[PDB]
Image (cartoon, rainbow, N blue to C red):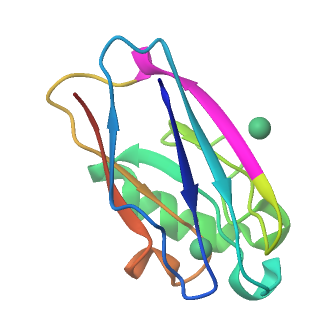
Amino acid sequence: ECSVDIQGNDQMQFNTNAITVDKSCKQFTVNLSHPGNLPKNVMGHNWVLSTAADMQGVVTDGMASGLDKDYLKPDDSRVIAHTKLIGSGEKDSVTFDVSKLKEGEQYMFFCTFPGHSALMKGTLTLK
Ligand SMILES: [Ca+2]
Ligand SMILES: [Cu+2]
């Protein structure tokens, strides 16, 4: 109930492209880990959640903020929730309120490390 375990690996892949959140959930938790051996500054990953329309800007601003900010704009109002940036062998979790999500909206999740969102993205939907 109300959580998903997700991996980002050394091939610039997340192990899901569609996350389902049961609608009765008050808080939803994403548990990110990084198998593999590459360090954070070479193939670090985070998990970041925004509306479909906000994704591109979150990504572009993230790249501009740089590594030392985990490739995310500090207090970006468009980020519904995010993990830390992690490298191999690390993990991080985040929990966010399900009330921050609305029926009929389309949410995307992605990694903001530069370039990774080309393949490391997917949908998040209420079920
Ligand atoms: Ca945390
Ligand atoms: Cu990544």
Q: Magenta span: helix, strand or loop, mainly? A: strand
- The magenta segment is 92-100
What count of labels does the image hold? 0
* Residue 111 x, y percent position in the rendering: 54, 65
Quadrant where the C terminus sits is top left
* Residue 92 x, y percent position in the rendering: 75, 49
Q: In the displayed structure, does residue 43 sit left or right of residue 11?
A: right
Residue at the spot 80% in from the left edge and 82% down from the top edge:
41
Q: Is residue 12 above or below residue 20?
A: below
Residue at the spot 74% in from the left edge and 72% down from the top edge:
66
Quadrant assignment for ligand 1: top right
Q: Nearer the viewer, residue 89 or 73?
A: 89
Q: Nearer the viewer, residue 99 or 63?
A: 99
**Does the stretch in magenta take in 40?**
no
Residue at the spot 48% in from the left edge and 41% down from the top edge:
78
Q: In the displayed structure, does residue 50 sit left or right of residue 47?
A: left
Q: In the displayed structure, does residue 66 sit left or right of residue 26?
A: right
Q: Is residue 5 above or below residue 35?
A: above
Q: Is residue 98 above or below residue 59?
A: above
Q: Quadrant of residue 24?
A: top left
